Image: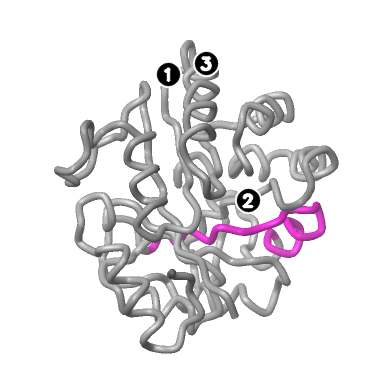
């Protein structure tokens, strides 16, 4: 099974929030330059997540997408408060390959179908933030602030039915930790969907990526562990290939 390594970049006002430790870059906080560098060292796909204030947010995200599409030749997603079809459409047309949606999809699951009808399922990534509550995996919205009362098991099935292309499974039980991806959650979700599962939250060392792939993840996404250079991307790819994981190098 081919496996993918993804890097996520959190952005505000056109800048990478908290930057990165790559001293070789002209501007280690420029999301375009940082994303281009990642694409040259072994990242397979990029995610750009925007948290800009509402008044400049739409134009900021559109300008980001346009610049990234010109400079980078790997697929990328954009996300962060994409609430309706028109917003998703303008970002895809401006250059993004995929949009990543969460709270708006939970509140209006037909948004998944509406985007997929024009852009295909492959353009729709649903990010599912989940946490254990009273012994059950529950779906959370609004950056983890709201327990929806929807079971993870039910939402995964609905997301596929509505036409999503990929699911990013983010474990709130691992946010800020470096103890590993939530492999129990990945194993819980794996039999429920045919879609690619992207693990998110908890990665602290290269072996954690191996564990996530053994759990059934098709891709593993991380952020600060790469930006602060706790894990080197090329070392990670060499490690995974050494231990039998079908990852891409050259």
Residue 8, percent from left and from top: 41, 48
Label 1 element class = loop
Residue 9, percent from left and from top: 38, 43
Image vertical order of residue 138 relative to residue 11, above or below:
below
**CA neighbours of label 2 inside 10 A, class few (<14), some (14 to 19), many (20+):** many
Residue 172 part of the magenta-drawn span:
yes
Residue 50, percent from left and from top: 45, 32
Q: Tell me: 158 left or right of 38.
A: right
Q: Tell me: 61 left or right of 163.
A: left
Q: First in sequence, mark 1 or 2: give its number.
A: 1
Label 2 element class = strand
Checking the image for residue 178, the label placed there is none
Closest to the observer: 214 or 250? 250
| Magenta highlight range | 155-173
**Residue shown at the point (71%, 29%) measured from the top left:** 89
Q: Residue reaching furthest front? A: 250
Q: Which residue is mark 3?
A: 59
Label 3 element class = helix
Closest to the observer: 93 or 212? 93
Q: Which residue is mark 2?
A: 126
Q: Tell me: 21 left or right of 249.
A: left
Q: Nearer the viewer, mark 1 or mark 3?
A: 3
**CA neighbours of label 3 inside 10 A, class few (<14), some (14 to 19), many (20+):** few
| Contact check, label 3 and label 2, Cβ < 8 Å | no
Task: Measure the C-alpha gap from mark 3 to mark 2.
Answer: 23 Å
**Residue shown at the point (45%, 63%) measured from the top left:** 5
Residue 152, percent from left and from top: 62, 63
Q: Which residue is mark 1?
A: 53
Task: Measure the C-alpha gap from mark 1 to mark 2.
Answer: 23 Å
Image vertical order of residue 16 relative to residue 213, above or below:
above
**Residue shown at the point (81%, 58%) measured from the top left:** 161
């Amino acid at each position: 099974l081919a496996k993918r390594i993804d890097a996520a970049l959190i952005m505000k006002d056109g800048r990478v929030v908290k930057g990165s430790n790559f001293e070789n870059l002209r501007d280690s906080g420029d999301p375009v330059e940082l994303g281009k560098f990642y694409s040259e060292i072994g990242i397979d796909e990029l995610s750009f997540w925007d948290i800009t204030a509402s008044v400049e947010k739409r134009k900021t995200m559109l300008e980001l997408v346009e610049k990234v599409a010109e400079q980078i030749d790997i697929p990328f997603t954009v996300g962060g408060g994409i609430h309706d079809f028109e917003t998703a459409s303008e970002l895809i047309l401006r250059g993004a390959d995929k949009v990543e949606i969460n709270t708006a999809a939970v509140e209006n699951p037909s948004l998944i179908t509406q985007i997929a009808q024009t852009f295909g399922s492959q353009a729709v990534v649903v990010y599912i933030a989940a946490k254990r509550v009273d012994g059950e995996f529950m779906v959370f919205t609004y950056s983890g602030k709201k327990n929806t009362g929807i079971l993870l098991r039910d939402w995964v099935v609905e997301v596929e039915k509505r036409g999503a292309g990929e699911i990013v499974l983010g474990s709130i039980d691992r946010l800020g930790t470096k103890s590993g991806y939530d492999t129990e959650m990945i194993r819980f979700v794996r039999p429920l969907t045919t879609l690619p599962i992207i693990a998110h939250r908890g990665a602290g060392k290269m072996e954690h990526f191996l564990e996530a792939f053994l759990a059934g993840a098709d891709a593993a996404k991380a952020d600060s562990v790469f930006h602060f250079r706790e894990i080197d991307v090329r070392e990670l790819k060499e490690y995974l290939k050494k231990h039998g994981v079908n990852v891409r190098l050259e």
